[PDB]
Length: 258
Ligand SMILES: [Mn+2]
Image (cartoon, rainbow, N blue to C red; front, side):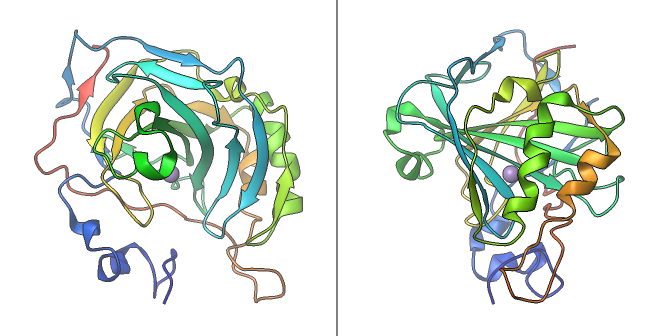
């Protein structure tokens, strides 16, 4: 029936409705650190989020998205392996039912407790919907989360989860600054890939940061309290909304560092 992360509609079934699931540039992947090639020609990333305008937070039944106003060049990403400017449209997370799993990308097969995705679209395309039809339409910044100390900048998000518990619920969410979610270092790995949920389009340049951010156990616990279901439907906790690693096939992972 419709896709999700259960036994009957989980990632292993997606190819029946979205054949691109078995495509040549699917994500996520395992990052083998010894085989990633250092590329001295890659430039430092440029993150400009000082003018970021968040608007709302929504439970879409598969994760929670914080959405931003992308009608102008307010929060953009440029540099790194990118040509042109990419505007932030939304961020969301993938997490596990246990601390030993939850991330989509893995590093030398290591899984983290969660993974944050900041989604950006190439402004040359004019809108998100046109950008997903292009090979260089999106740029996703992925950041791993490990359990340790609490992340202060994530608390405003944790606190509103109670109000968007079930599928379809949304809440006003203004003045949230995503700079509070960045690690200290911007060193990264990059490779050409796809969206990690249906429609699985191969329109993404992935930028995965080497340095994880720490969150407290209590912070991650509140994520696991969300529901996949809609209000008044039987309760299915929102946990393990991550796609396993896909074959690298003909792609090279490049590193901005050595
Ligand atoms: Mn994602």
